[PDB]
Image 1: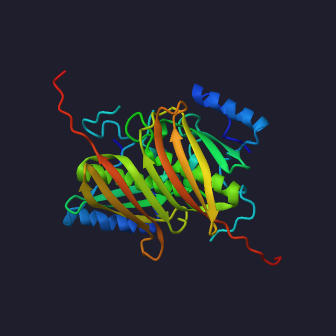
Image 2: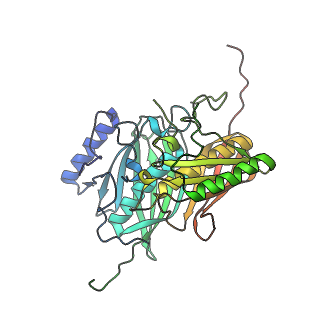
Image 3: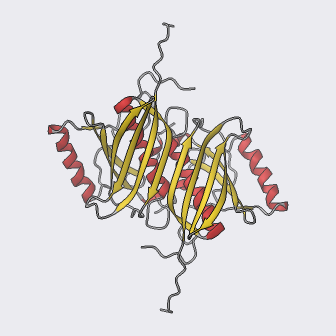
Length: 186
Length: 186
């Protein structure tokens, strides 16, 4: 229903500007904007596992939680997440909690892995933090699939300011490819 | 003010039981229960950095977000976090998002590092996931300081079910020790 990965009044100037740039890329460069719904339910067709919200949309009040949008490039198997952490995501006063960046990375890795190769289960997440993120500022997260091997997708991420004069963190993630199962009709 | 790391109606039976066991440990074994306030503000005396909530308390509605309490053992430099992720922390339907576990680990590492050696900045977080956490169930997170060297605290964590028949993840974290600065009176 509601796509939360669309602008609202809380988005900072830099986030809006970069969003517009990526929108243009969806017109002439093969990029696609991912929707972001209130949960994953009914949004992963055929998923078999062993009131509710997806974690990165746990806060629905604009500006206070995770504000973000992910763009995906299918041919290149890369994505970019524009992430603006709000004041309910704080660690030390005035800055985003490291765990909020970890969460946003895991979510971006997850969506990217799923679209690139039907990965979903996070096998590993390794993050090296470089600088604190000021609350309400734009974090640009560049994610790429480095390889797909042994039923696993390997990805890397760099999170930085728009002007790239501040790097916030670098990370790697490994995701398991979902198993395809051929069942008889019920 | 309000200590969120106290029981409420949302805590599952296992979480309450283990909480009581750790309360007893605070009586006769040197353990201490950490308070959990709505934010870190005014709760880290003398901190100098380069409406709001700490990320793990971003949701205040009982049972829906992070339900947790951390116990710390000062002599052993170990802690245990009792963590019950609620339905706003979901990843795939019915299970906690990997990023919510990452966040809870980072927060537990942070509090433990600060009390054990005045660590605060997360330098690195490396997580190996083993199993999905069912929403509303108890995750027991054992954290230890392995060493303090070169102004860094090295910690490890194992997150598991109470009966230990399910391991959810293992992780390591490295935290920078805060600098002590001697300033002149203003």
